[PDB]
Image (cartoon, rainbow, N blue to C red; front, side, top):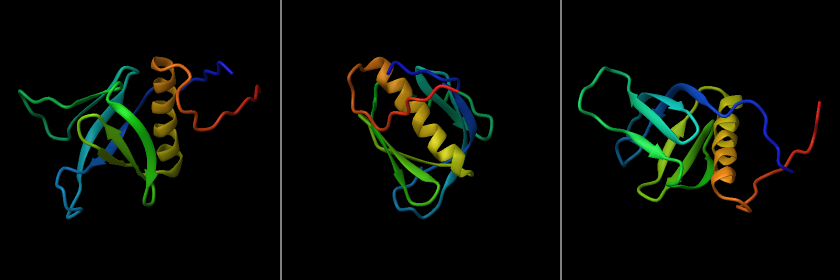
Length: 115
């Protein structure tokens, strides 16, 4: 165990679910540093806030096609990607940053392989 490969961050156009009726989707810029998820609105805004703390993230799972649902102590959020590799990537990135903050946590899948 004690794995750790490159790729602890990720940033790209993501469709956030603002409304509560799957009536539409709003695209917003997202970026991960390693502590929290900072995602701002596509358009330039002022006096606005929108950051999800890694601690809030209780669990992560996949949804629909090329989509996933991120549960947060506050309110579950749904993020959609444009590529398959991304969908899986994002999740992994989070799960990886979740195990660091929480030892002996719920394991998803281990891949012991070097080169």
